[PDB]
Amino acid sequence: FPDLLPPPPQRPLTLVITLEDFLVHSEWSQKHGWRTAKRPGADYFLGYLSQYYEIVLFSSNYMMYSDKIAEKLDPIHAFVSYNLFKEHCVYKDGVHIKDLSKLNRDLSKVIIIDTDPNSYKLQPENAIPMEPWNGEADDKLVRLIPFLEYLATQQTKDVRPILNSFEDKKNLAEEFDHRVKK
Ligand SMILES: [Ca+2]
Ligand SMILES: [Ca+2]
Image (cartoon, rainbow, N blue to C red):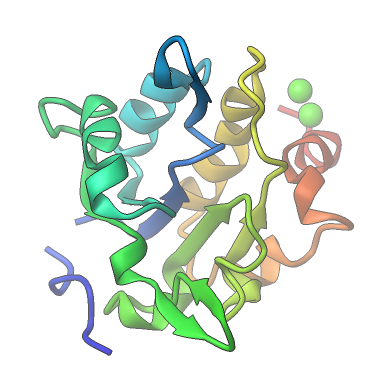
């Protein structure tokens, strides 16, 4: 399998985020066909965090299906460094996986945020799992920012010891809030 990204150009950390059920959510109908909603805070999340992270938007769908959705999130291409798709996943024991060791990045400096435990199966130590977004307006993206800002503003040398210090990474933003007095 090919390496997927050029060598770093620069930001101290790389943030790999899934598209489907994290930034957007799609539903099909007879009346309208496929329709896609954008989560509250998505534009701000990408715009603000791009100042601290190299952002890689890693879609779980084939390019032909999600290419345009991804583009709408950053039409002028100012925030997202790279777009990857299902074609870039490796296929192992019948599941597709976002193999971070193919990103040509130091894995002490990579975070992946995904909603499908298969996607981070090869690097669970780099992962922040998220409950899939259902399309209902919520503030979960905004709540994730303080931890991500913290990682970037403290260095950080290796994100993994901190990431894996939580009781339940699915509840990371809330636990981090209780751990820190701003
Ligand atoms: Ca707090
Ligand atoms: Ca708080």
